[PDB]
Structure formats: C-alpha cells, structure tokens
Amino acid sequence: FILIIKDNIILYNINDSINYLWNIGYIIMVVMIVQVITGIIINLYMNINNGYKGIIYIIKEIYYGYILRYIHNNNSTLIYVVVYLHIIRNLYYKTYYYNILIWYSGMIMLYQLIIIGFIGYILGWGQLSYWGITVIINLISGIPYLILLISGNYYITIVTIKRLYIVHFILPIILIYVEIIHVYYIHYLINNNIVEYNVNNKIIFNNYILVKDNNGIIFILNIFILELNNNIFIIADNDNLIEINILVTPIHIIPEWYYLYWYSILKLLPNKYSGLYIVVNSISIINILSEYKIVISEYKNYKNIIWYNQIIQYISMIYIGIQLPIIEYINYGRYIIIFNILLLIMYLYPKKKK
Amino acid sequence: PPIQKPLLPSGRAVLKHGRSMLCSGNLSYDVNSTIKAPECKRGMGFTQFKRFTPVPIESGVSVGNRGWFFPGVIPYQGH
Amino acid sequence: TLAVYHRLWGMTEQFAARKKWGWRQVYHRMLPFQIALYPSLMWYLFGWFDDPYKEAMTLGIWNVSKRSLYFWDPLRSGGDKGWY
Amino acid sequence: IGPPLRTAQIGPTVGGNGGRTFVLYLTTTINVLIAFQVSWACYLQPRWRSFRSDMLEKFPSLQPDMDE
Amino acid sequence: SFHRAFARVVCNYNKSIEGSVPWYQVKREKSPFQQVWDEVFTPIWFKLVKGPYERWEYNALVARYRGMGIMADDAMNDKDMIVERALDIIPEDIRIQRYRRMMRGAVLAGRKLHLPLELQNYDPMVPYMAPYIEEAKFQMQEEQELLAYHPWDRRLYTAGVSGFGETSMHSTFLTM
Amino acid sequence: KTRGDPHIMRGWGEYVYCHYEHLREPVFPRKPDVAKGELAAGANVTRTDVWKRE
Amino acid sequence: YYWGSTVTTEMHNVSPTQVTRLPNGMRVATQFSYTDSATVGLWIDAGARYETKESNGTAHFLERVLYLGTKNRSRDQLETEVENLGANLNSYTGREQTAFYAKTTKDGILPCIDILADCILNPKLDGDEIEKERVRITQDLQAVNQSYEELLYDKVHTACYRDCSLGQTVIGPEENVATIKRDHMVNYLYNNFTADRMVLVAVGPVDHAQIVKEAEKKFANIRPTAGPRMLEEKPYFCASELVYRNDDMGPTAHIAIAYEGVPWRSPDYITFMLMNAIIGSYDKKNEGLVPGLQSANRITQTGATRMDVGCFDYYTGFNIAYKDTGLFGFYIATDEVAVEHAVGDLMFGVTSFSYSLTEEEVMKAKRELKTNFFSGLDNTTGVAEDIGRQILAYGRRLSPAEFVERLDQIDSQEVQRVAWNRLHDAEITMTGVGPLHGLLQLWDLRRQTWWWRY
Amino acid sequence: PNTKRDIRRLGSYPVPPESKNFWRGRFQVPGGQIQQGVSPMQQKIFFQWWWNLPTRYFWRFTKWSDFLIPSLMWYTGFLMCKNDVEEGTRSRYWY
Ligand SMILES: CCCCCCCCCCCCCCCCCC(=O)OC[C@H](COP(=O)([O-])OCC[N+](C)(C)C)OC(=O)CCCCCCCCCCCCCCCCC
Ligand code: HEM
Ligand code: HEM
Ligand SMILES: COC1=C(OC)C(=O)C(CC=C(C)C)=C(C)C1=O
Ligand SMILES: COC1=C(OC)C(=O)C(CC=C(C)C)=C(C)C1=O
C-alpha cells in the first residue's frame, strides 16, 4: 500500500488556485476518524442497559472521561457542520455537473450519517431521545407490523437500544469504506477549480496542499477546543439529561440542531406521509439538478442568486423547527417550502431559445 | 450451395503492376497470380481455413488505437 | 446524385426510434426473469402476511393445521387456543 | 519535432453510462409521484371533501345513519 | 404472441412518420391566445424583471471575463465531450493563444488579482470556437447514428473494461 | 460594448449565457446565409449546397 | 421479421443447366455461356471417407498419377497434346468428392473429353511414376512441410469424428503411403470410379446434345455401377480436444473451435451459411474500407477494442457440410497472450445468435453472402465447380433465384431458432497448434455457449 | 483524467506505478512557456499577504454585495413573521 499512498498523497497533483473551501473534505475525514476512536473508547466504560446512568459514571468516575463524553457529542455537531458546509460549497461551484459520480458517492455517506447520528442520540437514554424515536418510528406505522420488528416490543425499551447500538457501532466503519470510494473518484475524476476551465497549474499535495489543509484544521481545532471545554455555543439540548418517564411528554420533542430542517418539514405539512415524502424529496432531488440541461456550460461563476436563496431557505427552516408549533410559523413555513420547490425547479429546467 | 471464395474479400487489384491480361501468364495457375487456384498437396478443403492475405502476420500489431497514443508509447492502465 | 445523397442522409433520420427499440428488446429479454423473482419474494415475505392470506396465496395448501408441531410461538402450537 | 498533427478520435467516444440514466429515471419517478401525493392530500383532497360535504345539503341520498 | 404485435405497431407507426418536417422547420403562426399573452405580459415582464435581471447578470459576466483576461469560449470545460472533440481540431494559432489566456486567468484568480484595466478593452463574447464546435457535433452525430443505434452486447469485465460501453481501461470503480 | 445578446435564451430556468448546445441537427438543415456573414460549419455544409459556386 | 423479396429480373436471366442421365447412369450437366473458354470435367462421388483404414491415401495417390500417362499415350505425349490445345488439366481430391477438370478453349472441348476419359478409364499406373510420387507425397506428409491452417483443418476432423472414416485424412498416414502399390490404385478405380457416381460437367460455348453424344461414346466401357455403399449411422460428434502445444514455433497461435453442423440437404443449411457469413472474417493486415474499431461485424468491432491492440490477428468462420453431418465453427490466428480474449469473443458471438442478433447484422450478412456466392459464378471454372458440387450434394443445381428466395425467408428469428436448437449449450471441439498457455480446458470453453444474462 | 490529447505522452519510458495519477493530469503545452521562481528561503514569505490585502477584500465585498437585495427581502420576511406570531398569540390568548 506504500506505493498506493505515494500515488495518492505524495505525487498527487492538484490545482494551485483552490480556496480554503477545498479543505473542508480533509477536515471531515479527520473529524470522522476522531468520532470512531472516541466512540470505541467510550464503549469501554459504557453500559447500554442504562445509558443515562452510564454517561454519569463516565463523567464522574473515569479518569478524563469527561473529555471522551464531550468530544463525542461535540465532534458530532462538528461532523455535521463540516458536511453541510461541504455540500453548500459543492452547490455554489456546481461541482456535480461533471463529477456526478463523486456527488453520488458523497450522498451515500450523507444517508449513512443521518442514520448514525439519530441512533447515537437514543443511546443517551434521556427524555428527549426516547420520545423522539417514539415519534419517528410512528411514521412507518403504516407499513403493517414493521414498527414491531424494528422496536422489538410494543414500546421503545432496552430491547430497541441493544439493536440500534449495533447499527451505531458498525455503520460508521462502512461509511469509512464509502469514503475510499469517494476519494477514488476524486482522484480519477480530477477535482474542480475556482475557474470553470482546466488549467496546467497543478502542484503536489504533501508539500503544499497538506500544509495548507493543516492550517485549516488547526484553525478549526482552536474553535472546537473552546466549545469542547467551555460550551460557548449551545449545541446539545438540556432535556436529554432528564430521566425517561413514559407517562410525561417533554416540553418540546425536537431533534438535534442538525435534524431540524427535516423536523420542520414534517411538522409543517398537514399529512404525515406527505411530510415524510417531502423529506425524501429534499435528499433525492438534489441528485439530478444537472440532468435535464442541454447547453455546453456548467452554469458556474454567475451571481448564484438561486443558490443564496436556497442556503437561506435551509437556515430559515431550522429556525421554524426550534419554534413551538405556533400557527403563524406554520403558515410562513409552508410558503418557504413552496419557494424551495420553485428554486429547485429553476435549477432543473432547461432553457428555450429566443 | 458451396462458397468458393474467402469470407474476407481481397479488395485489391488482381493484375500486378505493369502486367496486363495479355502478359500476366495464366492467372489460373501462375505463381505470381493473385487468383491462382490453390494447390491440393494434402487434399481439398483447407481453403475454408486459409488466410489469403499475402502480408505475413505481425503478432500483436495494434489496430485498436483511437489516436490516444503515439507509436512506441506503452499505455499504462489504459491511460 | 443529390438524390442518392438525400437517401443516404435520411437513412438514419429515425435514430431515436431505433435506439428505443433496441432497449425495449433488451427489456423484453429480461421479462422472463420475473418467474423466479416474484415467487422468491413471496417465499421470503410469506411469514409477514396474515394467516387468512397465507391460505389464499397457497390455494389452500397451507393452513393453521400445517404449522409445525413446535411452532415458533409455543403457546400457539396446534392452533391459536393450543391443542386442547 | 514540431507541434502534434491534428487528428479526430475514432469513435464512438460516448457510452457506458446507464447507471446515471437509471438514477435520473428513478429519482424523477419517485419525485413525480411524491408531487401527486402531496398535491392531493394537502390541497385537493381536503377541498374535495368539503365540496362533497356541502353537496350533502342536497341530501337526496346522503349516507344513511345506521347501515353499520 | 403480444410482442410480435407490438413490433408491427411500432414498425407501422414509424413508417408513417418518415420524412416528417421537424417542429422547428414548420412555419408556425402563434395562437391568438399566445398573441394576447405576448402583448400584455411579455412587454411588462421584460421592462421590469427579465430585462434588468438578465442585463445585471450579463454585464457581471463580461466584467468577470475581462478581469480574468479570458474569452467566453475559453471558459468551456473540456470534461464535456463535444468540447474535447472540438479541441482536437483547433488550429495551433488559436490553440496557443487560448492556453496563454487560460493560464493568465488562473494565475490571477489564484492570486486574487485582476487584469490591469489597460488590457481590458476587448469583446469577450467573440465566438472563435463556433466552427469547430459545429464540426465536432457533426462527427459525433454520425458516430451516434451509424455506430451506436442499439444497446450492444459485449463480454463483461474483460480487457479492463466493463463491457457496458466505455472504451477506456480502468475507468470505473468496478474496473479499478 | 459587447456583441453578445443578454436575452438569447428564454423560459423558466437559471440564467445562462453560452453559444453552444448538444442538440441533434435535422436531416435537411437550414441553408446558411454565408453571403451576409453567417457561419457554415458541420451539418449545414455537408447536408446543404451553400458551398456551390456557379 | 420479413422485409420483402430481393429476387430481381436479372436473377432469372441465366442460361439453364441441362442435366441428363446416360443409360449407364452417368449424369451429364451443361450450361451455355457467352465465353471463348470452357471447362469440361468429371465430378466423382469418391474420396478419402470411402477408403478403409488400411488403404487410406490411395485416392490421393491415384489423383497424383492419373495424368502421368495412359495406356494409349505417354506422359510426354499427353502433356504435349494438352499444351498444343492451349488447355490445362486440373484435379483435386477431398473426403467425399473428387474432380478431374480441364480448362480449355472452345475448340478443345471435345478433344479434352477424350483426354480425360482415357486418363480415368485406362490409367497407366507405371511403377516408376508411383515411386517418384511416393517421395513427393512423403515429403508433403511431413507436418513441417504443411501450413498450420492445413494442419488444423485435418485435426478438426480427427478430433470430431474419431469413430468414423470422416476422421481420416486425404493424404493418409505415412505407413500406408509407404506401402501403396499399383494394385491398390487399380482396385480403387474399379470400385469407386463408376458411372453412377460420375457427373460430366461442361460450361461454356457448349451444346448439350453434342456433349452427351461424345460422353456416351467415350465413356461407353465404364463400369456401370458398383455395390451400394454400406449403410451407417449418423457420424458421432466427439466433443474432444487435440492441442499441440509448441512454444518453439513463434508468437502466433492457431486455434480452431468446432460445433456440430448440418448435412448438405438439411433444411437448416442455408441458415448455417448465413450464420457463417455473420461471423465473417477479419485480418489486421487487410482491414478493408471500414476499420475494425468501426466495423458493422460485432465480433470484429469488440475484438478490435481489446487492450487497445485488438485480439484477432486473423479469424474466419467455417461451415463444412457432408452427406450426413457437418462442422460449424471458427478459426483464429492470434498472439499468444490474446488467445483467451479471442476464443472468448468468438464464442460470445456465436452464443449471441441464440439471444440478441439484430436485423441490421443479418441483412448486411445476406448481402455479403450473396455478393460472395454470385461473384464465384463469374468464370466457367467457378460455374463448373458449382454445377458439379451441387449435383453431387443435392442431385440438382439450385438456381440463384431459388437461393435468394430461400434466403429471403431466413431472418433474425430463424437464425435464433436454429442456433437455440443446435448451437446453444452445445458440445464443442477445440484444436490448436502453437503457444497455447492461454487456451483453457474444453469444459471451460464449453460453458461459454450459454449466457447468465437474458 | 485530462483529454486524450493532453495525456498523450511523447516519451516511451513506462509510467511509474506511483505516478499514475500524476501523468493522467498531463497537459500538452502549446507554444511553450518560460516558468521562473525563487526558493522561499530567499524571499519575503508574509509580505504578499499584506500587499494583496486591500484588493482581496475590495473584490470580495463587491461580489458579496450582489446578495444584498436578496438578504433584505429575507430579513423583511423574518420581521413580518415574528410580529405576526406575537400579535396572533396576544389575540388567541391575552384578555
Ligand atoms: C426486499 C426484496 C429484495 C429482493 C432482492 C432479490 C435479489 C436477487 C438476486 C439474484 C442474483 C443476482 C445476480 C446479479 C445479476 C446478474 C448479473 C449477470 O447476469 O451477470 C452477467 C455475467 C456475464 O455472463 P453472461 O450472461 O455474459 O455469460 C457469459 C458466459 N458464461 C455464462 C460462461 C459466463 O454473469 C455473471 O458473472 C453472473 C453470474 C450469476 C450470479 C448469480 C448470483 C446469485 C446469488 C444468490 C441469489 C439469492 C436470491 C435471494 C432472493 C431474496 C429475496 C428477498
Ligand atoms: C459517523 C460517526 C459517528 C457519529 C456521527 C456518532 C454520533 C454520536 C452521537 C450524536 C452520540 C450521542 C452523544 C450524546 O449522547 O449526546 C453518540 C453516542 C455514542 N456513540 Fe457514536 N457516533 C459515531 C460513531 C461511533 C462509533 C464508531 C462508535 C463506537 C462503537 C460510537 C460509540 C458511541 C457510544 C458508546 C455512544 C453512547 C455514549 C454517548 O452518549 O456519548 N459511535 N454517537
Ligand atoms: C462523510 C462525508 C464526506 C467526506 C468524508 C467527504 C470528503 C471529500 C473529500 C476529501 C473531497 C476532496 C477534497 C475537496 O475538494 O474538498 C471531496 C470532494 C467532493 N465531495 Fe465530498 N465528502 C463527504 C460528503 C459529501 C457529500 C454528502 C457530497 C454530495 C452532496 C459530496 C460531494 C463531493 C463532491 C462533488 C466533491 C468534488 C468537489 C470538487 O469537484 O472538487 N461529499 N469530498
Ligand atoms: C439538505 O441538507 C442540508 C444542508 O446542505 C445543503 C444544509 O446546508 C443545511 C443547513 C445547515 C446549516 C449549518 C444552517 C441543512 C441542515 C440541511 O439539511
Ligand atoms: C427526533 O425528530 C427527528 C426528526 O423529526 C421529524 C427528523 O426529521 C429527523 C430527520 C429524518 C430524516 C429521514 C432525514 C430525525 C433524524 C429526528 O431525530
């Protein structure tokens, strides 16, 4: 494998005109490894029979256990931040027009990540986690008997925790394999540049791009260390530190911040399945945004007005999700969904000739 | 009915350069004739397998270059 | 001679219809693979269906009396109310 | 010596991309069928029921009380 | 057999549309309804939305090209197969200046600089690639029609190719 | 000023200015007006008689 | 699918072939042509197949000594007389058929009939001539003095027909060649060269009545008939391998793969002719107007792409027919390292006939099949071979119009039905000479006669 | 990889296994170029960041100003929604 490493790290040529937005991917890979390692180490001290009491025993009795607990929670937030920012970049520079295979490989990892994060929340075994899964599982309540097969009982119990835990342990290793398929296509299908064309300005990776990529990762580390030890930003809801009580419903059953876009979609649409279906649309339509075009152009380096309104649509929907189900927010949020459909139609539609 | 010619048509001129229908000899058996009926030294039938192309085979000569390589350059993993 | 050229140009006019036909011919040659797929699906999904539909799906050949002597639910071997 | 001579590539130089066409057709189909469901259940269906329920003011043959 | 019947239907329906004039070569008079629409909406829409928005975008695009010092046709990505087939046959004079402009543009863009204004007084929308794009499309259409009219069958995953059509070895993940 | 037409393309869709497309050409292409300076290349030269002189 | 009739008016405008049976049983067939040259010969129903194991090689020896002098002439006199007529005497010997035909001018037609009759009926098999020919035959028998296409043609029959006489070669084994004597040849003449098995073919400026009169006069004393041939069961096709691995003969490997074919008179024979045409032939050193990379032939096109070099230096299909059996397959001459790709592609091509064969490829093949058959009927010798070979094979000559009529009915569906019945999942025989490390076992190649797809 | 004309190699020396990706990114340079440079050990390594500082931030803010009007419409909507929520809550409840 040493020759492979030399071909893909030491003699790998990349354009010298790339920004720091081309370093996001390096950070995902590094922060992903950290999340696997910390997870395996935390597992050495965790009892999934009661993860509420288990998390307490890690933070109070294990030496430096608090580091492991808070890194694993905060580095998840970090993983999703970098991933979501990696997508925003790919949309801005339309890096899906000629490198769709790379885009497809990435979306597979996005799907896997969406499952890993949710199930990890439930391993915390707190009020919010319990009621949240109890609400999501009841969306596939239409498919007969499938809730029972997934849950293992008529209500969420440790039986469900013992099985989802295995998915949370194993699915990350598969994600790492898909990361190789992703880096494989990137290295074959050369990366896109800040300029729309292809230019002979490439420089080796280890001597230049890795030094710059490390300056980026160390910048993010400074900020992540401050959050890790001082909670400068509230990235974890406090109601997950309340012991589960099946009789009392939490003040608000919401997911982590990185699931609020899809939570809002499901709380805005009036039919449960319509909401589930509009969540599918969000994570599927974005994979065909260049397929119907017919012009010899990649629609790149224009003012990207449609892109800006899409990125804001995401942020605004996350806000509506935090807010309680006040009727006013529901009406306004339904307009934001209609607007998103229209913006996505704009990307899809080919143009006629004057 | 029987097929009396190879499946690959020659597509070349029958008469040789400077030789005419008057001075080409007898094209049925002349050694230089391109249409001389072959010799049955070991019997009749082998002409169904015979390669009638005059130029000797050059093993491995390339015919699948779409203009992607210069002569003498070895492709590596097809690139 | 332009007449000859007109025909030689026009002989490929209907490329989209010929390529559609080729793919349909491929799809036709995959249709027979259903005879093994659909039964294999029901074979795997049999236990999901209710007893009433299991009987119809098998044309009566399977019924509650055909459940194993040692049914996966011990309290329901020999019927929903047990043997006796 | 000198610049390379111009020559066209023997083709076809396209093909072999049927997986991408499958994804296109699958994604369009799914999202076209999601549009029908969301348009129906969230807008049409509700309004249709209201009309039928206000078409019961005629009550020539409205639904019977028992008929259990 | 129902397939044999469908084959006759397809054969007869295509024989009945041979030689048909394409929709864009038919002299077409717009419907009266469209005419009313094109006298009320189109004028106002152009004066208030389309016109200003598309001039705003176009002028920005010209400025971006002028800053990079490149032409519009330079911006084409050679990952597009029509562009590649055209770039095979461009003359060396055009080719040399095209490379130098693209090189200068990437240097300036990477170093976050812009072309000096002294060099920016040129028309970036000159279509110098047009002749060769049209030739390339013609060559590709002939190959499409004469050599790719059927989904051919080939031995799969042999000689470094999947057998599903691609012609370069080791050009897919499953062909490594 | 720049010779391009900002409004060369219409309809719903994201704004683009480009000179070329991938669309197939007809069996009998429109004869280009080379006298006035229109381009004749590809299908409109082979499958037309715009090149013939007296 | 049916696309119409390709028979034309010009196909009907051909002089008829008149066939009459003489009282002794000899058929006389003639066709008039507006030519100044003619071809008159004797197509006999004899060959190596109708020899016994101990006498194999006698027919070939006799064919080499029949023109070396008669009982009424001498070799010098005979050669002088033919040269004075401005004519040339030819002859060939096969497994099932033999011929002795002269190409002469118009004035030499009847004189040549006399010469051929004397050679066939009164051969002077001088011992000196036999001994000299024994040396020449022995030298030819050496495989070093035989081409690789001739070697694999013979070994295909040896491997496929182990149980019957069709496996015998024409030249014969060296042991028999060493022992053949005049008595052997005299017996062969007496038993096999009889009137009931001979056809006198005259093509050119000829009159049927005159040819018939001369034939009856010159062949009056021929033996009328011989005993009927022993009835035998269908020649058993042995799916075997006979490979001569030799890594000391250069880089090129010669491989022949055979399926069981059909007899001459089979209703499917024309379908097998078309299938042979679809396979076609290709040589890297004579590619034609269309390159391999852009060929309409699917086997050629896919082969030309392999490794960006091409996996077929040469290949050709073959369709060999006999009275009660046949062989259908392909012959390859390719680089050592390319053999696995080459045999794999041609077998994939033959297997494709049973699944996915396009109307386009069939129609192209029909035209090139008809362009090859008709062009073969251009000269008198070509016509004479066609008449003599077709009367022996069928008892009649099929007209060009009839051939086209029957070929019109054959379509992609008919090819698929025949291939599915006979070639799909069928037993094969592989034979080869050269560097053949890449050639797999017979069972491995035989699994390539069916597909997991479709 | 790059176009087949770009990756076509003049030399007959085999591509090293560790340099496969490197030579799949080859370009056929037309007309030639004269590339020059100096080692970073003999140069000022931070000055250019300062020299390019004003122009970098000018050309960045001029491009990002394109989004101003979009940004203002979205903030106007955010304020309208906030006030609508408050008035609606005070109307449903709040005697
Ligand atoms: C929730 C419901 C899910 C339902 C999923 C059902 C999955 C069914 C899978 C069946 C096997 C699919 C194999 C790949 C597709 C075939 C590709 C192909 O033809 O390649 C051509 C290639 C090329 O072959 P060829 O056709 O060109 O032939 C060349 C000549 N020979 C034959 C000598 C090679 O063939 C192969 O390499 C394929 C070999 C066959 C592989 C079959 C694997 C079977 C595995 C077990 C199946 C278990 C079923 C479980 C069902 C569960 C249901 C819930
Ligand atoms: C894609 C990679 C992963 C992500 C995104 C992910 C996500 C998370 C999340 C969000 C939590 C909840 C933290 C909290 O309670 O607030 C969690 C819990 C947990 N994860 Fe992971 N995880 C990853 C991989 C792994 C791996 C590989 C392991 C090791 C088998 C692991 C082990 C654990 C354990 C034991 C817990 C429960 C303890 C805890 O609450 O901190 N995780 N994970
Ligand atoms: C587990 C999450 C993922 C990781 C590990 C990751 C990793 C990377 C890496 C290392 C790069 C190359 C360096 C770069 O240019 O930044 C890259 C490129 C790319 N990724 Fe991802 N990625 C992930 C998620 C995604 C997702 C979800 C998508 C699709 C929405 C995606 C699409 C792309 C694309 C299109 C490129 C090419 C960008 C360009 O053309 O250069 N990635 N990724
Ligand atoms: C569709 O996937 C999503 C993104 O990528 C495009 C987002 O940007 C966002 C928005 C992210 C942030 C940090 C506001 C989310 C949550 C999302 O769901
Ligand atoms: C607890 O509530 C949650 C949601 O609420 C509807 C979600 O949408 C989501 C997102 C779901 C999908 C399918 C993207 C998750 C994971 C979640 O945890």
Image (cartoon, coloured by chain):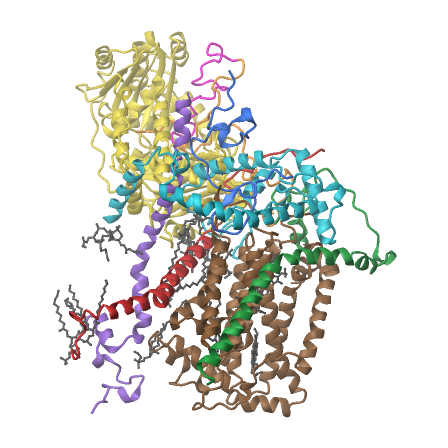
Q: Pick the residue in front: A135 or E63.
A: E63
In the figure, is residue H3 to the left or right of C62? right
Quarter of image, ligand 2: bottom right
Identify by letter the chain in red: D
The residue range painted magenta reads: B19-45
Please provide percent x and percent y for residue G60: 37, 28
Q: Is residue E153 magenta?
A: no
Q: Which chain is green?
A: H
Q: Residue at x 74, y 53 (%)?
A: E111
Q: Nearer the viewer, residue A113 or A171?
A: A113
Chain C shade: purple
Chain painted in cyan in the figure:
E
- Which chain comes out blue in the rendered image? F
Q: Chain A: what color?
A: brown
Q: Is residue B26 above or below residue A133?
A: above
Q: Is residue C77 left or right of residue H54?
A: left
Q: Which chain is yellow?
A: G
